[PDB]
Amino acid sequence: VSVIKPEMKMRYYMDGSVNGHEFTIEGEGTGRPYEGHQEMTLRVTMAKGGPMPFAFDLVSHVHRPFTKYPEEIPDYFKQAFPEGLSWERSLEFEDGGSASVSAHISLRGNTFYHKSKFTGVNFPADGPIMQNQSVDWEPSTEKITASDGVLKGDVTMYLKLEGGGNHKCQFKTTYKAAKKILKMPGSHYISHRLVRKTEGNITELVEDAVAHS
C-alpha cells in the first residue's frame, strides 16, 4: 500500500460515557506501521470537569494498521487504505460491567484520523474500573478469523489490578474495510503488548502488535 509509510501520524477523538459519566478524549501520536508500533498522548475531559472517575484501561484498547505482518499472511488492515477501516467491539467484564465501542479510521496525507463512540454500563460502584484500581492490560494473543470479506477478533483480556491479581474481560471485535479487500487472509493470531503511563487526565500509550501463525 503506497500510502502506508514507515512513519505515520495519528489524531484521535472519542465521545464516551461510562456509568453515566460523559467525557471526550482527544490526542495524537506517531507510529511505525511495518513494525506494529504506536505511541500517543491522550487527554480526557469529563463533561462535569475534574479527574476521570474510572480506570483509563477501560478505553486504552480503543489501530490495526499498526501490526507487524509477515509476508505469508495478507495484511487486511493496511490493504484497507486509503479507503478506510472501521471496527466494532463488545466488552464483557467478569463482574458484570460491559461496554460497546466502535471507531472509524480515515487517512489524509500520512495522518490517520481515528473517531470513536464508547458506552460503558453496569460497572459495580466498588469494582476496579470505577475505583480506578486497574493499572494495565496484560499482553495477549487475539484470534483472527475471516468471513464475508470482514475479520473477526476474539481475545480473553486480563486487567492487572493495583495490589496484584487480575480481572477478566472478553473482547469480541469485527473489523471492516471500507472497500472490498483484494487479498483476504486466513485464520491467524495477533499478539499485543499495550502499556499505559498516566498522570491525571493525561495518558500516554504504547502498543506493539505482531501477526503470526
Image (cartoon, rainbow, N blue to C red):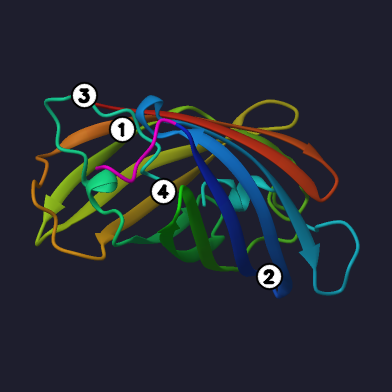
* Disc 2 to disc 4: CB gap under 8 Å: no
Q: Kindly report the distance in space between the C-alpha atoms of the residues bearing marks 2 and 4.
A: 19 Å
Highlighted range, magenta? 1-6
Q: Position of residue 131 (x, y in %)?
A: 78, 50
Q: Nearer the viewer, residue 91 or 39?
A: 39
Q: Position of residue 38 (x, y in %)?
A: 52, 34
Q: Relative to 135, is 76 above or below?
A: below
Q: State the SS at label 2.
A: loop
Q: Position of residue 44 (x, y in %)?
A: 76, 57
Assess disc 4: are there few (<14), some (14-19) or many (≥20) residues with their C-alpha within 10 Å of its C-alpha.
some
For this orientation, the residue located farthest to the right is: 50
* Identity, as a three-letter code, of the amino acid under mark 4: Gln
Query: Which quadrant would residue 189 be assigned to in this image?
Result: top left
Name the disc covering residue 170, or none: 4
Residue labelled with disc 2: 19
* Identity, as a three-letter code, of the amino acid under mark 3: Pro
Assess disc 1: are there few (<14), some (14-19) or many (≥20) residues with their C-alpha within 10 Å of its C-alpha.
many
* Identity, as a three-letter code, of the amino acid under mark 1: Ile
Q: Kindly report the distance in space between the C-alpha atoms of the residues bearing marks 4 and 1.
A: 16 Å
Choose the circle earlier in sequence order: 4 or 1: 4
Residue labelled with disc 3: 70
Query: Which quadrant would residue 165 be assigned to in this image?
Result: top right
Image quadrant occupied by the C terminus: top left
Residue at left offset 37%, top offset 44%: 64
Name the disc covering residue 190, or none: 1
Q: Position of residue 120 (x, y in %)?
A: 58, 66
Judged left or right of residue 66, residue 186 is left
Choose the circle earlier in sequence order: 2 or 1: 2
Q: State the SS at label 3.
A: loop
Q: Nearer the viewer, residue 97 or 196?
A: 196
Q: Kindly report the distance in space between the C-alpha atoms of the residues bearing marks 2 and 1.
A: 31 Å
Assess disc 3: are there few (<14), some (14-19) or many (≥20) residues with their C-alpha within 10 Å of its C-alpha.
few
